[PDB]
Image (cartoon, grey):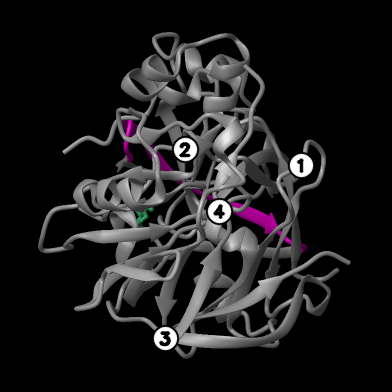
Amino acid sequence: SFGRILLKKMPSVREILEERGVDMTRISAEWGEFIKSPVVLTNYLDTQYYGEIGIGTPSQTFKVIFDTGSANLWVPSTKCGPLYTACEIHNLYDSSESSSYMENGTEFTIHYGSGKVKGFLSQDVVTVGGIIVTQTFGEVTELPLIPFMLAKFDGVLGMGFPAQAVDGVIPVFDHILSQRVLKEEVFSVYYSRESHLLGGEVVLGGSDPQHYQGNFHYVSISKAGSWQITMKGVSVGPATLLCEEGCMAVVDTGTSYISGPTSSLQLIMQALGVKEKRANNYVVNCSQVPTLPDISFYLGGRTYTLSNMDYVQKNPFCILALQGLDIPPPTGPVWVLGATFIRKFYTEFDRHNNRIGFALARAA
Ligand SMILES: *[C@@H]1O[C@H](CO)[C@@H](O)[C@H](O)[C@H]1NC(C)=O
């Protein structure tokens, strides 16, 4: 258990609002917006998994999201003022208790779907999966209410490329690579079946052979500075409907729902046999779930199939784990294979070869 980080299941901000009796129209309209330098593919509304890291000497524990969509580490600060009530329900980084703290002070702004996180940079020791790196990270002093007033995670560990990082900060994984401690310059991400207790695993330096079956097959990165691959077909049932001419697709551990363009996804929802739409999202009567056809994605000359049980979430109060999202050019129309895709297919992110590997996930 050297370079492994146990991911733990948490109620998502949608699931917290659902359990408090909030209407599905209100949740999407007020907590799930996508506002018009690096690209945003998530609002953390549906994120269900966090890992724990330590920051400082002695180490102060934080619950963080492992987000391949971003390249920055940030956590709430004790410098976070009284105007930001969201800070008052989370763990706070206190430089006063760290002997390894070294100030920087340059301001940063990280944009995401529902809003923006502001603060200042600071250097300290960071322990992630038993590996100690000297990291520059964001001390957040302006944490917005949407969605962090109800989030069950403190902050975000970016697992993206250094080109995506704000203020040109060297990311956490890049520092781990500089140390030459890992067997491979890769990390892989496992989510187990959607249960109440069962969690997941991020492995640094390789892949856990317990959590996959058969063999990995790899797809090259098509855009240099991100986990982005060419998709050559989206199919409902036997019929291939979209992406024959070639779609860009991001594999993102940050968001759990698969994203596509609103027009392309509405076409899929028609052919799926699904009428009801709430903003970006699509709800369905739980009686008609077993009759839904399989969705498939064509990646690196192989099909990756999601069955009815893989892309639907039953919560007490059934919602499809797909949603509309239009990123404009030059970045272009993009799909996002979120954690729903990765739960089915154990994913290896490869930094040396600049490629992404997929394999059929399983339990032990
Ligand atoms: C703060 O961090 C940045 C990296 O984003 C670095 O280039 C800069 O030299 C640092 N500034 C100070 C004053 O330590």
Q: Are marks 4 and 1 in contact (CB under 8 Å)?
A: no
Disc 1 is placed on an element classified as loop
Query: In terms of secondary structure, what is the magenta stretch mainly?
Result: strand
Sequence order check, earlier mark of 2 and 1: 2
Which quadrant would residue 120 be assigned to in this image?
top left
Q: CA distance from mark 3 to mark 4?
A: 19 Å
Circle 2 SS class = loop
Measured from the top left, where is residue 3 in percent x and y? Answer: 75, 70
Label 4 and label 1: CA atoms lie apart by: 13 Å
From the image, tell me which residue sits under label 2. Answer: 44
Label 2 crowd bin: few (<14), some (14–19), many (20+), radius 10 Å = many
Q: Say which of 79 and 289 sits in front.
A: 289
Tell me which segment is drawn in magenta. Answer: 112-130
- How far is mark 2 from mark 3, CA to CA? 28 Å
- Where residue 269 sits in the image (x, y, percent)? 34, 46
Q: In what element is the residue under mark 3?
A: loop
Instruction: Note whether ligand 1 is within 8 Å of mark 2.
Output: no
Tell which circle, 1 or 3, labels the residue nearer the N-terminal end.
Answer: 1
Q: Are marks 4 and 2 in contact (CB under 8 Å)?
A: no
For badge 1, the amino acid type reads Ser
Query: What x and y, as percent, mark residue 47?
Result: 55, 40
Residue behind mark 4: 340
Residue 52 percent across, percent down from the top left: 71, 46
Identify the mark nearer the N-term, 4 or 1. 1
Say if mark 1 contacts mark 3, CB within 8 Å.
no
Q: Is residue 127 above or below residue 196?
A: below
> Which of these two is toward me, 107 or 202?
202
Q: Earlier in the sequence, mark 4 or mark 2?
A: 2
- What residue is shown with label 1? 195
**Dot 3 corresponds to which residue?**
300
Residue 196, picture quadrant: top right
Secondary element at image label 4: helix
